[PDB]
Every structure is written in C-alpha cells, then in structure tokens.
Amino acid sequence: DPNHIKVGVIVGAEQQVAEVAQKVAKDKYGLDVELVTFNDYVLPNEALSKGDIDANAFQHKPYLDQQLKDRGYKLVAVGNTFVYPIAGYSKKIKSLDELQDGSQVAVPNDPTNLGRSLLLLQKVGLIKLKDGVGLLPTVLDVVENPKNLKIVELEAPQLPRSLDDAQIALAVINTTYASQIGLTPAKDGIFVEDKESPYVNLIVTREDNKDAENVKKFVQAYQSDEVYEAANKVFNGGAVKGWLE
Ligand code: MET
C-alpha cells in the first residue's frame, strides 16, 4: 500500500502525541499512518530492522548509536521530535533532605539512560563519577557516594512500579513511563535534568527507506505546531521542541 506507513511508538502520553501527528498527516497529505504500539525500548528497533514497521519514534541519538553497536542494525535518524528532560521521583520522600543512608535508588539499566541517570545523580550532588566517562558512566565509575546509596538497575518500563517497592526511595524515570502513572517532572519531580542535553528524541528508519516519500511526510506531520501544543499540554511543559522552527 503506497499510501500507508506503520510507525512504532510507546503507549501512554507519547502515543497520544503520535495520534496528533497521525491526524496532521491525514489532514495535510491524506497519508494513512498506522501506529504500532510498544511498551519497551527493545522491540521497536527489532520491528523496524525486520521490516515489520517503517519507522519508529521513541529514542534519542545516544540510545540509537548504542543499538547500532550492540545489535548491528542499519538505522538512521530522519528527524528530531522532543527533548524530555528526565526527573527523579519518589513515593517515600519529598526532598533529598529525607534520603536515608543505604537507600535504594532505581535507574534504567540500558547503557545510555543508565549513564544519563548517573550524570543526573552527580548533578544534584548525591554521587561523584570518575573523570572521562562522557555519556556512558556505569555504577563502577562511582567514586564518591557518602550516603552509601544502592543503585538498582531496572528495565526502563519497570521504573514506575518500582516506586511502590518497600526499599526504593528514589527512581530516575523516563518521562515515557512516568507519564503512564500521571507523573511529570514539573509537578512531581524532586530534581530534573537541564533542558539542554543530548537527548532529543528521533524519528528513525532503516537506511534503505530513509528517503521514502511517506517517511518525509510523517516527519513533517510530527514536526508541527499542533503536535507541539499537544505534547506541551500532556507533558506539562516537559517536552522541548527539537526541530527547526
Ligand atoms: C529509548 S531512549 C529514551 C527515550 C525517552 N523518551 C527519553 O527521552 O527519556
């Protein structure tokens, strides 16, 4: 079907935003966009690589690059979407003043979002990392940890439910999944990453279909004021436009 494109997205608020892009694509081009929904960060790139979908819209470039290295995919970015500054959340404390020694702190376990989380924990002064780590520090790079915090690495989609675990005092959670239980950085975050970061999300395709006319249309539909306005609402200001104005 030459007027049909399948795009992989994550359930929750990101799916809602993608639905607006779907609408713009229909209204502006009469393009038939099908959203294929996922609730993890691994299967969407598998689906794309295998040709089960044409594009996906869920990852930032460090993540993409790591996926190319680790899985050997031939994928490429065809457009920016939003930066989603990541936040630390808790259902046990309201401030770092209350963080007890020995507390478990949950973070994503994939290399780039793990690194990102550790950099955030360093930024707010809870830990110090070795020099030269760049974007990919690991827990082995922690050189100061005065509260003797225990970093608990979890699959990203598990981070929202981790908040209810009896020992998890703090969790760094992608807004993707935080939004599934109605949390946003501005409303619920104890601390939040700077808007300026390398983590703008992407629309990604295979090398072989990066220039497909339907891909170009979808990118233009997503990169629209209508989509921004929707994102800014549902993410309560936690979505920064990543494309050229
Ligand atoms: C799969 S990389 C992480 C993407 C997620 N939406 C974020 O920007 O935190």
Image (cartoon, rainbow, N blue to C red):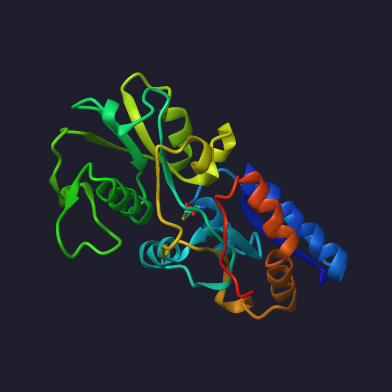
Placement of the C terminus among the 4 image quadrants: bottom right
Q: What residue is shown at x 63% (from left), y 55% (from top)?
A: 8
In the image, residue 224 lies at what x, y percent?
Answer: 72, 66
> Relative to 116, is 206 on the left or the right?
right
| Image quadrant assignment for residue 242 | bottom right
Numbered-mark total: 0
Q: Nearer the viewer, residue 63 or 197?
A: 197
In the image, residue 218 lies at what x, y percent?
Answer: 72, 68
Q: What residue is shown at x 36% (from left), y 62% (from top)?
A: 70
Q: Which of 68 and 31 is in front in this view?
A: 31
Q: What residue is shown at x 42% (from left), y 27% (from top)?
A: 163
Please say if 23 is above or below 177.
below
| Image quadrant assignment for residue 202 | bottom right
Q: What residue is shown at x 40% (from left), y 51% (from top)?
A: 193
> Relative to 183, is 199 on the left or the right?
left
In the image, residue 108 lies at what x, y percent?
Answer: 38, 44
In the image, residue 4 lies at what x, y percent?
Answer: 79, 65
Q: Which of 209 and 119 is in front in this view?
A: 119
Q: Is residue 32 visible?
A: no
Please say if 80 is above or below 125.
below
> Relative to 146, is 189 on the left or the right?
right
Q: Nearer the viewer, residue 84 or 151?
A: 84
Q: Which residue lies furthest to the top in this view?
A: 166
Q: Is residue 206 visible?
A: yes
Please say if 149 is above or below 3.
above
| Image quadrant assignment for residue 197 | bottom left
Placement of the N terminus among the 4 image quadrants: bottom right
Please say if 189 is above or below 202.
above
